[PDB]
């Protein structure tokens, strides 16, 4: 009902959907190869998944 | 050792770090308000978190 509650429900729904989008992200394959071959660290790589 | 194994370890590390970056994403507040007020659905909103 309240703005806090309705926005908390929306946040949980967004995050739930986003978990799957993250696991299935089309750049994970290439970023993982970049971390494994030493051209990037995993923190920088993880940041590059996001807008 | 193998490319598959080293890239699987990197993927798991990237995903682990990315989980936290996602939970802390600076656009979640505004996107959640957009879903709660009817200007966006939660799937489109979740997509907008990603590059």
Image (cartoon, coloured by chain):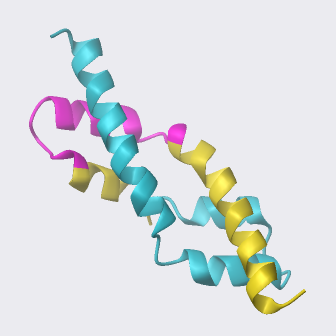
Chain colours: A cyan, B yellow
Q: Which residues are magenta?
A: B23-42
Q: Nearer the viewer, residue B2 or B10?
A: B2
The picture places residue B31, in percent across and down from the top left corner, at: 29, 40
Residue occupying image coordinates x 75% and y 64% = A42
Residue A14 in the image: above or below residue B18: above
Quarter of the view holding residue A7: top left
- Left or right, B19 with respect to B3, comes to left
- Up the image or down, B31 lies above or below A28; here it is above
Give the residue at x 19% y 37%.
Answer: B35
Residue B11 lies, in percent from the top left, at 68, 70
- Residue positioned most to the right: B1
Q: Residue A10's spot in the image, x, y percent?
A: 27, 32
Q: Is residue A14 above or below residue B46?
A: above
Q: Residue furthest bottom?
A: B3
Q: Is residue A43 left or right of residue B49?
A: right
On the rendered image, what quadrant is the C terminus of chain B found in? bottom left
Q: Residue A29, image x and y in percent? A: 59, 81
Residue toward you, A41 or A19: A19
Image quadrant in which you'd find residue B34? top left
Image quadrant of residue A48?
bottom right
Q: How many marks?
A: 0
Residue at x 22%, y 14% (from the top left corner): A3
Quick one: quadrant of the N terminus of chain B?
A: bottom right
Q: Is residue A3 visible?
A: yes
């Amino acid at each position: 009902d309240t703005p806090e509650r309705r926005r908390a429900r929306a946040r949980s729904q967004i995050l739930s959907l986003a978990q799957t989008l993250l696991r299935n992200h089309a750049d994970l394959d290439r970023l993982s190869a970049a971390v494994a071959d030493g051209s990037s660290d995993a923190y920088t790589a993880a940041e590059r998944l996001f807008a």
